[PDB]
Amino acid sequence: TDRVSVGNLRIARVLYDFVNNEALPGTDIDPDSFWAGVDKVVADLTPQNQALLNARDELQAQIDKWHRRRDMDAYRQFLTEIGYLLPEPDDFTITTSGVDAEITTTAGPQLVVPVLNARFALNAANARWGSLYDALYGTDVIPETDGAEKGPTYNKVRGDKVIAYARKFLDDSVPLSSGSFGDATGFTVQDGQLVVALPDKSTGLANPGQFAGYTGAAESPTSVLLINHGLHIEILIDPESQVGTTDRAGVKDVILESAITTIMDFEDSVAAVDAADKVLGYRNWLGLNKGDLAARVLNRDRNYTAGQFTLPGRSLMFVRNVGHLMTNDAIVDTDGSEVFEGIMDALFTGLIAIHGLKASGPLINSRTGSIYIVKPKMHGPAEVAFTCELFSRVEDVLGLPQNTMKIGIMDEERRTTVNLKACIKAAADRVVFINTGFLDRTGDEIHTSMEAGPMVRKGTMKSQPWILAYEDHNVDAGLAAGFSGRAQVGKGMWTMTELMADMVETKIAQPRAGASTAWVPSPTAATLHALHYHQVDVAAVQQGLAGKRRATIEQLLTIPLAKWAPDEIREEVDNNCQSILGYVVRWVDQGVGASKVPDIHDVALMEDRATLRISSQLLANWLRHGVITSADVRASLERMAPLVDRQNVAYRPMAPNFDDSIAFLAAQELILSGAQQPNGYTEPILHRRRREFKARAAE
Ligand SMILES: O=C(O)/C(O)=C/C(=O)c1ccc(O)cc1Br
Ligand SMILES: [Mg+2]
Ligand SMILES: [Mg+2]
């Protein structure tokens, strides 16, 4: 067989060769003891890994039959009875140490990209610094009304509104003692503080401490760096430029620190179903931790006059492993059982990250000596304990000190939401953030209460009582554990990549709730979301909330049951079957784990496996209570399958041959058998069908 024999494992050759030729050299770990640890850890941990998965199926099975009989008094008592709801520990504080300042202190956007896409990943690590002019001019933040519409050449009417918008931002972030940046006619620093020239007057910063440094001669600085809320603002002064020649202070651009941290993703935004897929990922992740990823390059750090100092130039990177559910046949055991993909990610992504700790690739990742892993889709504290013990064992195999691997706990399952304090206590010496995964969180809420009744519509979940408590309950728990100045309190993702006007308008709510950070789709959306953290003082908002328990158990357990006309239904099912179809074609046919599919209302939504978990779970729920039928679902399936194809070279249509499309027939499975996946997860059906398409295409 092609696989390579090591203890009780048969490792696919391509993985085995990658780890030996690319990963291990540099880490001073002997390739034979490394594989010995791998075989040993896997054999050690697979049992209670599988035990925990059975506990999900068991706890769930109790809930399902409960609702086909049975109103929160009996319910809450029954959940704590069966071990779902567990006791709350005593108040405590996290002890995680040696964490980069990006996570303990700075507040600001958090970006997520698929790690299998290298040029995206390059742009994301490069996204710690972003032009504000390009994000304002490039999007709908400036309305494309009047004579300010983007064209094939640069539009100057639009250009000055960019400048005026940024001039205002400068006024509301770094105030002058008297006057406005819009009437600014010169910049210079004389005797250590910057003097801004005005028409008649000359004024300085109201707080002269927000001056951080500059480029060029202090006479005619090529730029001036400013700080506010720990976030850096660079004004590039070069009147040579096209934009510089027009601006009344020679200003070329306004650059904001944008992507403070990025999350390189191995889970819901990627398709990776055999050992060849994971190694493109792993190779990209290795390319980043070395600092030699190219397609062009990672950018270097930036230097300033204060003498000279220097700032980070790339976004500090996390990785997101997969959770505890899926297996992957990149490794099989002697009788053929696929090995748990969560354990593989920890060993392999961990080993790789030793390179992002040294320079001999040239570029360092963590300056405090930590490795940052996000663990999605945990179900309770005991699942957190296991991830901890798993990381502790990987550390031994890899020879690094205990607790180098830190956790990014994802509050995206119901059983961790109501036991959140127990969860963070479990990781208490490794946690570096908690984050409301509200899409994954919504799919669990539906699948957990599937037998309770018909669910409210998808749009309506945004305002349901459970969700609102869930968002405030997380911030409560974080601050009560010491997260301020220690660990990020993080919130969820803006999916609408073309509505930056609405994003700039409404996403301010998240930092106003005390979020240290929130998730972004793009380097551009990251820059705009950064405007929100110059407005709101996240650190001050956090202190106004400590103690304030604005949420109880009963608000978290309120199930979004409904109580609709035959227009509101046919519009929901069609809407759903369209975003399911449009995501799954690119998923099954091309191994693309994230795509922008316009919903029914011509809104470009960025989909992943969480959003598809909500959609398919939803129809699934409406089918189980007879809101609609199987043939009605099939109708909307066939109704829209022509539409995504015109909405979509080297691509495969779906209509009229619905039987002969593994992508179409997968989407149909995802709904019609939707209810029977463990916790409504979508990896099984997607992984079996992705591998199927490959198998046909190889014949
Ligand atoms: O809230 C969650 O479930 C969470 O973890 C976020 C995502 O997984 C995600 C959702 C949509 C999207 O377009 C990109 C992503 Br990265
Ligand atoms: Mg999620
Ligand atoms: Mg302030």
Image (cartoon, rainbow, N blue to C red):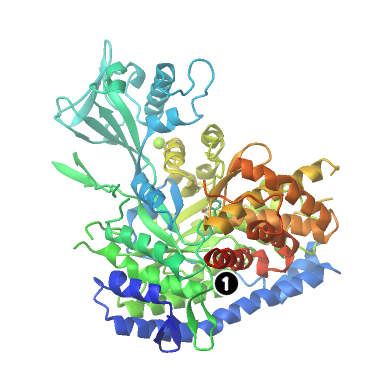
Image quadrant holding the C terminus, namely bottom right
Quadrant location, ligand no. 2: bottom right
> What percent of the width, then of the height, locates residue 7?
41, 89
Write down the quadrant of residue 617 in the picture: bottom right
Residue 329 falls left or right of residue 684: left
Write down the quadrant of residue 307 in the picture: top left
Count residues near mark 1 (Cα–Cα under 10 Å), then give few for <14, some for 14-19, many for 20+. some
The foreground one among 174 and 167 is 167
> What percent of the width, then of the height, locates residue 460?
72, 46
> What percent of the width, then of the height, locates residue 112?
46, 52
Residue at horizontal 57 percent and vertical 72 percent from the top: 325
* Amino acid type, callout 1: Leu
The foreground one among 184 and 344 is 344
Secondary element type, mark 1: loop
Residue at the extreme top of the image, as rendered: 200
Q: Which residue is mark 1?
A: 325
The foreground one among 231 and 542 is 231
> What percent of the width, then of the height, locates residue 253?
32, 28
Is the residue 438 above or below the residue 677 in the image? above
Residue at horizontal 54 percent and vertical 33 percent from the top: 505
Residue at horizontal 58 percent and vertical 66 percent from the top: 696
Residue at the extreme front of the image, as rendered: 699
Q: How many tags in the picture?
A: 1
Q: Is residue 473 visible?
A: no
Image quadrant holding the N terminus, namely bottom left
Q: Is residue 288 visible?
A: yes
The answer as to whether callout 1 falls within 8 Å of ligand 2 is no
The foreground one among 644 and 373 is 644
Write down the quadrant of residue 431 in the picture: bottom left
